[PDB]
Image (tube, grey):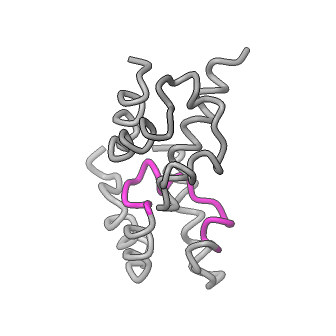
Amino acid sequence: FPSQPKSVEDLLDRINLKEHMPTFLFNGYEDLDTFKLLEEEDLDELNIRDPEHRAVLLTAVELLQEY
Amino acid sequence: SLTVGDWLDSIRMGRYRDHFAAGGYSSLGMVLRMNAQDVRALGITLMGHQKKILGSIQTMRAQLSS
């Protein structure tokens, strides 16, 4: 779909979390078919601790299951 | 093709062909018995790659059970 996130970078840009882009792309989450596997415990391992960031990321992951 | 090397390429994890081969996983049937420890012991360290490989194994076992 033309309107869909094209990459992890595009998705993080859309949800205003580009600060986490090196964290995901240096820890094996460089492709959207892997990003869509994220769960809360995976954000702990990635040291992503801000509850607002965490909720935003897990909402975006739910939307990719639709994809 | 239910080759280990074809399975890895299908999930974009062909970089681990030599890791699986060295660890003795010559069939997919041997891969389907793996757990997270088996994956780490091949020398696979990137978190998301561990997660993608195990998730694929979990799904393939469910699709062959029934």
**Is B34 placed left or right of B13 in the picture?**
right
Residue at 37% in and 76% down: A22
Residue at 54% in and 46% down: A65
**Is B21 placed left or right of B64 in the picture?**
left
Measuring from the top left, give residue A52's x and y in whole percent: 61, 81
Measuring from the top left, give residue A60's x and y in whole percent: 52, 61
Query: Is residue B16 positioned above or below A53 on the image?
Result: above
**Is A46 placed left or right of A4 in the picture?**
right
Measuring from the top left, give residue A8's x and y in whole percent: 37, 62
- A1 or B14, which lies in front? B14
Residue at 64% in and 26% down: B61
Which quadrant holds the N terminus of chain A?
Answer: top left
- Asked if residue A33 is among those painted magenta in the image, a careful observer would answer yes
Query: Is residue B15 positioned above or below A51 on the image?
Result: above
The span shown in magenta is A28-44
Residue at 54% in and 57% down: A61
Which quadrant holds the C terminus of chain A?
Answer: top left
Residue B63 figure quarter: top right
Query: Is residue A19 positioned above or below B54 on the image?
Result: below
- A41 or A60, which lies in front? A41
Query: Is residue B10 positioned above or below B38 on the image?
Result: above
- Asked if residue B43 is among those painted magenta in the image, a careful observer would answer no
Measuring from the top left, give residue B21's x and y in whole percent: 42, 35
- B19 or A27, which lies in front? B19
